[PDB]
Amino acid sequence: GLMQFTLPVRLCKEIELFHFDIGPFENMWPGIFVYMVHRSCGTSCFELEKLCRFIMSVKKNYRRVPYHNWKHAVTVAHCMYAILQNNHTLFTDLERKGLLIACLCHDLDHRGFSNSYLQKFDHPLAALYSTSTMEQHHFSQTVSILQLEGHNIFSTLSSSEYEQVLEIIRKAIIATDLALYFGNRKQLEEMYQTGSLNLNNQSHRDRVIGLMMTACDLCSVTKLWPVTKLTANDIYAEFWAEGDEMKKLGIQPIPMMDRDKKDEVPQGQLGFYNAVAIPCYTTLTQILPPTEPLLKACRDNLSQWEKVIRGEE
Ligand SMILES: O=C(N[C@@H]1CCN(c2ccc(Cl)cn2)C1)c1nc(C2CC2)ccc1Nc1cncnc1
Ligand SMILES: [Mg+2]
Ligand SMILES: [Zn+2]
């Protein structure tokens, strides 16, 4: 109860910032996550013995892949931490609880392959879940760990609140299917621009949480250039491996997943910042102004990718 977590001064300061990198010391990441839950939610939110055990079962069920790994799970929870800390009054006690756990669980048991590849490969998960194939798997894994013994971190909630929080987490994890981002933002854009957006509307709240999850999921594009640059290597490591597996199915992959088409990556990143990233943080800033630093950082990396094409690096 009186056992606070405390980080070194540089991390204690820098972890409040949006562009925070959790660093290469894996054994610190669980403590970083418990510090964030304590500040963002409260020392009373979770039983420390259960949370710690929950955290370590989740870690175990992430795989050793270049990008969609344990570090990504924690990085995505940090972004969600920063948003909730800068938007202090807007979110309920169950949301702040649900959302940090949703972020940590969002990519449980990821194999480094897109939904497309599972469909074309005719993976068993594709027959079980026809859309948002991995995301439904991710949520299924989350429920599996919650139900392990001594892992029910929500055991103080009423039966009804417990159902609410698992509904928050399900929708939250499904929203990280990028296929669903495009329509979600467009609907939020119109609701803002016609001025009919309404945070008391539960249908509206879900969409906003959906956008927050995309924002957090893509947050490697909102770091200082060196972190974003080096994370781009890990993502394409996964992309190029999948392309190889596409070729093995007798399918020429899209250039994004073809390693013989590295030259085209800089231009591919512009399209992505223009088509996906900037629109995502713009709309998010419009609905939550104190998230503006995610937009600024995103623009800074977009500018850096233009410099790459101009041969200045
Ligand atoms: O870039 C991403 N998608 C782009 C789509 C088009 N792109 C493309 C097109 C043509 C060529 Cl020839 C090369 N590439 C790539 C990306 N996607 C995801 C989720 C799987 C959806 C997450 C992060 C991402 N970027 C990222 C950048 N930096 C640090 N971390 C992640
Ligand atoms: Mg995912
Ligand atoms: Zn993810």
Image: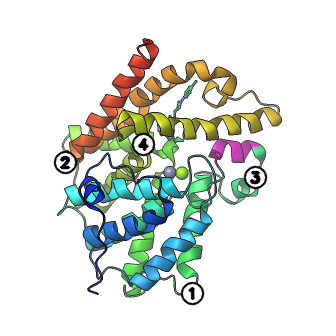
Mark 2–mark 1 distance (CA, rounded to whole Å): 39 Å
Amino acid under disc 2: Pro
Cβ at disc 4 under 8 Å from ligand 1: yes
Give the mark nearest the N terminus, 2 or 3.
Answer: 3
Secondary structure beneath dot 3 equals loop
Could you say which disc has been placed on residue 131 in the image? none
Query: Is 142 left, or right, of 48 in this rendering?
Result: right
Secondary structure beneath dot 2 equals helix
Secondary structure beneath dot 4 equals helix
| Residue 134 magenta-highlighted | no
Could you say which disc has been placed on residue 290 in the image? 2
Amino acid under disc 1: Glu
Query: Residue 148 versus residue 163: which sits nearer the camera?
Result: 148
Give the mark nearest the N terminus, 1 or 4.
Answer: 1
Give the mark nearest the N terminus, 2 or 4.
Answer: 4
Residue that label 3 marks: 123
Residue at 42%, 42% (x, y): give it. 220
Amino acid under disc 3: His
The picture places residue 82, in percent across and down from the top left corner, at 28, 55
What range of the chain is rendered magenta? 112-120
